[PDB]
Image: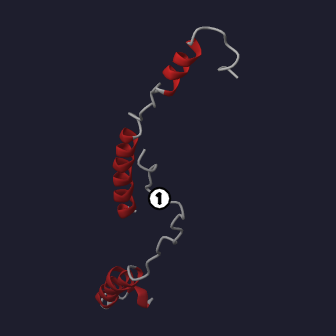
Amino acid sequence: MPQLNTTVWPTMITPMLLTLFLITQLKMLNTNYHLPPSPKPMKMKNYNKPW
Amino acid sequence: YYKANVAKAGLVDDFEKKFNALKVPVPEDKYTAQVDAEEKEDVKSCAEWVSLS
């Protein structure tokens, strides 16, 4: 079983860490979801005429 | 009608002399000037709000 060849293990451990923990994560941060725009048509800080 | 129908001694004359020479008191305002001033004050408060709006 080549999986048990413990000599090239450091060749798999590092670039995974360089891919699972740095690169791919750095692409999810660049996938943002904005809150959808429903600005209410009812925003009027008004007041009765001067009386 | 009252010169030729009263046999009282000249009393119709002095009643009518007291009438043509009567000065009925014309009532004076004393109350519209102070609401005009209130009106002026209002238009001031109005116009400044129209400016704000």
**A14 horizontally vs A43: left or right:** left
Residue B8 lies, with reference to residue A40, above or below; the image says above
State which quarter of the image contains the N terminus of chain B.
top right
Colour scheme of the rendered structure: secondary structure
- Residue at image location 46% in from the left, 49% down from the top: A48
Q: Position of residue A49 (x, y in %)?
A: 45, 50
| Closer-to-camera residue (A43/B39) | B39
Image quadrant of residue A51? top left
Q: Which one is nearer the viewer's eye here, A45 or B39?
A: B39
**Which residue corresponds to the image point at 46% horizontal and 31% vertical from the top-left?**
B26
In front here: B37 or B41?
A: B37
Q: Which residue is mark 1?
A: A44
Figure quadrant of residue B30 = top left
The kind of residue on which mark 1 rests is Met
Identify which residue is drawn at 43% across, 55% down: A45
Query: Residue B43's spot in the image, x, y percent?
Result: 38, 53
The chain letter for the residue carrying disc 1 is: A
